[PDB]
Image (cartoon, rainbow over all chains, first blue to last red; front, side, top):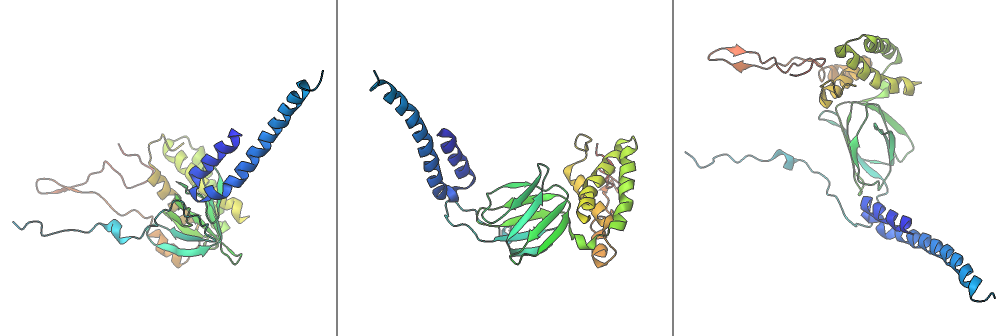
Length: 52
Length: 160
Length: 66
């Protein structure tokens, strides 16, 4: 997640003019990382709250 | 005494430098190149598709909308590529490349000669001289041979 | 390398320029360019009435200022 946002700053530091065109790819990478964590957590929440 | 009869102009003001831009939001399609040897340009704001420079860190390649970066030019070759697909190679002797986000390049050098004005036969003679000079144990000759070989090796590699 | 030997960046550039002037072909361009490497200048300073050379900064590129 941060490795995405951490990039966007540095890129924006080197090219502010491109800052508005890089944000979609940033949000996309964030969303996919977050979704992977979400499934990793969904196992656990699914592991406990239903299984006896 | 006259109260300051003279009022000289600043010579910097007679030049027209680019103004850098923040957040313009537009990418140039082709750069505006300006190569200068000691004082005289060889190219003045030419449209150019691409350019390729050599540095100590290594060889770089610049296109339109390249990030603002200022850096040395290692003594070697310099490739310009116009929109027509042709190319133009220039040998240089150091300098400083000033790139712009808006698309401007100022490659200020001490020398700029095309490869077409160089002959391999005359170069081959200088090579062994610079080499044997590097072999001679003496700080006055060794460094000079090292520098000459530094400029000659890329030429010997590129002409082939 | 040449850095700690004392010679500056600009003498290094001028030496590389002199080398490029050596290798390049015979033609009008070489006639224009040899002028941009050859050494003809001096320094001088006035004594009480006479001229004297300030030879602490040499023109020849192999040497090192002191």
